[PDB]
Image 1 (cartoon, helix red, strand yellow):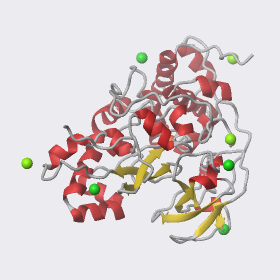
Image 2 (cartoon, helix red, strand yellow):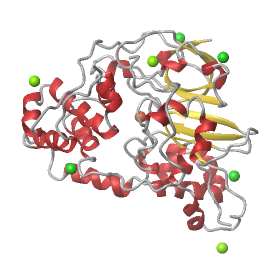
Image 3 (cartoon, chains in turn blue, red):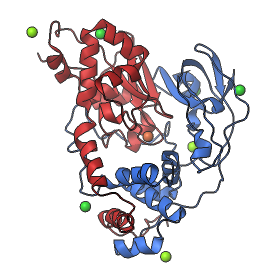
Length: 211
Length: 197
Ligand SMILES: [Cl-]
Ligand SMILES: [Cl-]
Ligand SMILES: [Cl-]
Ligand SMILES: [Cl-]
Ligand SMILES: [Fe+3]
Ligand SMILES: [Mg+2]
Ligand SMILES: [Mg+2]
Ligand SMILES: [Mg+2]
């Protein structure tokens, strides 16, 4: 999904709000802040209501202005609440009644997702690969800066996982694939307009093709 | 035009979500409190610091950490949520590694701790992939241009830690002394371990 969450390479932001080794304060800065992750795990591990990938995708589905003005942990409050409503576990009525006011949620999905690709290639360390020049409206774990770009494999994982574009929609056809550390030259991704060396993206097999 | 939607206070919304689930019996007794304790007390960059100090003083462990990070971490019992498939990346005299999750905040929680606000900021997520040298410089870390900067974007299930170079002036230090200078920011890759003058 080509949403505002796909921020890598966006220009115009200011300084990162940190200097190295500065005091970052407690893990949680407010008494509610442990709730979104804890309730995500209740939904994933205890209720079996959704996957972690569905949590990433429901946050990607926040209305874009809402995403841009919402602090990090609050996006997950909104995202887990939305999934609980979409899965029929909670109603928005009851959330707003308990909250004492408005509790707007992420927008509905405009894609049913897609299955794990039927045809893929096992790649080897050192092989040149290109990221498939594909556009996916639902969840995908490919940041747009690498779409269509060429890099070299530095690692093929020794485990396999469900394809995000399927499990992020709660589909039954996510299968399992390994992922690949693909090293791109900075210039491949950003031309002359970068001060970096290389960027390594961890890409599912189904996002790649031989170069 | 472009205005924020009306919202109840975020604390009210977060506790409403807890109460709506809890009041249906869907949240086991002590469940969120258990997670809060895990997140605050167990998931910690002191663990990644212990792994670095061991690698720095034990060539065999160093090799294991760099070839099978998961197995190395498992020896210490530090695998966990968002930390089940670990790759450690080695800094060298010509290479500085730095980690981000441009799409959200993915981090090797059990050995780095939960990510700090700054790592999850739009500023870091947008900028470090494209201008890591300027970002690190602004943050207080100068990387000379005889060094390639390599940014790992945490886009799938690999969870990374940086194994920084060991600074001169620490020869013979104990593992506890070395651990003290491996900070959270050294594990993420934005800082280089500092030796007192
Ligand atoms: Cl609170
Ligand atoms: Cl250019
Ligand atoms: Cl292919
Ligand atoms: Cl070294
Ligand atoms: Fe993330
Ligand atoms: Mg985009
Ligand atoms: Mg209404
Ligand atoms: Mg001594």
